[PDB]
Image (cartoon, rainbow, N blue to C red):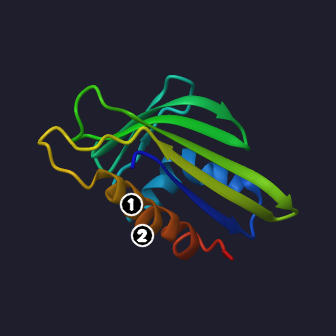
Amino acid sequence: GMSFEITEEYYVPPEVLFNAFTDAYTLTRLSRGSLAEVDLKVGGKFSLFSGSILGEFTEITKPHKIVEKWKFRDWNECDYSTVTVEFISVKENHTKLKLTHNNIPASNKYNEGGVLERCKNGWTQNFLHNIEVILGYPKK
């Protein structure tokens, strides 16, 4: 309803996956060219797809964990979801990626629903997909 969890393993070490979530130039490649902007610090803002997705870093524990406030700009001004991303070392050059997306609103500011699938398709179909296919990180 308001949360989902995605779990994936990559044959690459945690720091490289951590980079991919926090580095403007990697984020832009994962966005197929739309400018990602990143101020990488606690309280630092971020923006993907020219401000279509915005957020703020709230915890940066390199290279194991990040936590974010995170919204599409079309959500209510007040509404912010929480994204937590863990990069867990299974063994050498093998990382377990666990993404948790909580506190997803039932609808945007124009009372349109289907917000949860939109967040989930965003991760599976674009972002997490391109880590494999664009960045060339092999996945189970």
Disc 1/disc 2 C-alpha distance (Å): 6 Å
Q: Residue furthest top?
A: 43
Q: Which sits in the foreground, 61 or 75? A: 75
Q: Which residue is mark 1?
A: 122
What numbered label is drawn on residue 85?
Answer: none
- Residue for point 57% across, 36% down: 67
Neighbours of disc 1 within 10 Å: few (<14), some (14-19), many (20+): few
Residue 107 quadrant = top left
The C terminus, quarter of image: bottom right
Percent across and percent down for residue 120 are 41, 59
In the displayed structure, 35 sits above or below 120; it is above
Q: Is residue 128 left or right of residue 12?
A: left
For badge 2, the amino acid type reads Gln
Residue type at numbered disc 1: Gly
Element type at mark 1: helix
Q: Is residue 6 left or right of residue 9?
A: left
Residue drawn at point x = 56 percent, y = 44 percent: 22
Kindly identify the residue that appears in the image at 50 percent across and 22 percent down.
43
The percent coordinates of residue 127 (x first, y second) are 46, 62
Q: Quadrant of residue 34?
A: bottom left
Say which residue label 2 marks: 125
Residue drawn at 82 percent across, 65 percent down: 93
Residue situated in front as seen by the camera: 98 or 41: 98
Residue 31 rendering spot, x and y as whole percentages: 40, 60
